[PDB]
Length: 48
Length: 78
Length: 98
Length: 306
Ligand SMILES: [Ca+2]
Ligand SMILES: [Ca+2]
Image (cartoon, rainbow over the protein chains, first blue to last red):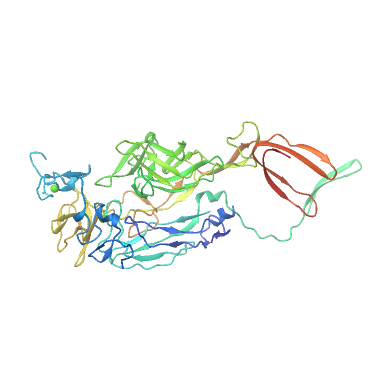
């Protein structure tokens, strides 16, 4: 997570996508349906 | 001690963020919100019955008295 | 830059939901109880604590990635090629030799 | 054409809005941005390309589809923006730099807006920053969101809508419950009271055993309109992929002009050269020795210096 190559695949159109991103989801809290979640900043953009 | 929000609990067995106490909705099976809240007249989406009850506008003039005063059903008006 | 798709959550109004694994990238879904979520109209479930919700999220290449995608490549000993122009007397020729 | 829980509305506080923004892209070299929105733009209420108007989910007692003209929309960040195109769930505009991007509608009675805190900057292509591309200069390979809406950037999946259980979609009877929908609307109702119960109905139905409206739900079987994966509309019990929609405004390779600061005046001396540089905007200088080692160095020069 948070580094270059956090998401990778054999080719951009390929379904063979693998990723490590520290994606984690918090327990819904607000009255309105929601899915609050957090993740490391896109490692590709961080390296950028 | 207080429950995790440190705020009022409804008898349904859950504490609620006190802001929701007068949001115009009740978030528990118990009488907890509008029972102790200030309510303005019904919204533009609603109908003001003569007893002051608020009912969905589409329900007004449908053939069934919805509000206890029945103001929603008047064959001379509907 | 990955795009974190958060497909609309699955809700159940009378029981739990299994975290059925998926081949999607970084698929890391979690199930939560006590959700009792609302929507623009109102509550979307029958009971109170008996309802549960599954939040599902994974990542796919953002649409723009098609252009700005970092092709990682391993490098192995490069073979030099050269385009040579050779001239010998009035005769001359051009060539490309690895 | 659904609706979503928008972080900001006309009131900074979050609220439900018909035009919730879902994603923002800005990989363009001209600062144009592609916005995906909950509303469907450039389609009529039927689903045909009436480019002059858009369709969006209701704001009242039933989830019907309403129409409005483009001229009441406005994509604005810090200030306003040149709206460059629109199609279905996607809007395209070129915007000034700002900390957030906002989509808004100004119908008076239906005046709404939606915002997503998103850092957009005045990115520039090339090796010399500029406020505005130059008229005379070198042309370099750049990428921009193609104004042609027919272009394809990719695709988004979508699904049938789930239950949209209005609070007014159901009723209570001073101790009892009821399912009062509009006349002739085939409405499915489901409710657990002592035990699980369900039924499809089209008129007011007195419920058995139930007492409080919160015990029950109800939603019509309106699947005619598909819905994007967006979080705020609960998925249907079957969430298989319903076709696709082509992402408009393809990121297309093209050419863009970049400025050329006045050529640096060289000065020649013993095994060393002096560069006198002049650029009113940040300009990248890079130097490397062609020897066994590069000793490469890079420096963003500004103004006039040596
Ligand atoms: Ca409440
Ligand atoms: Ca009535």
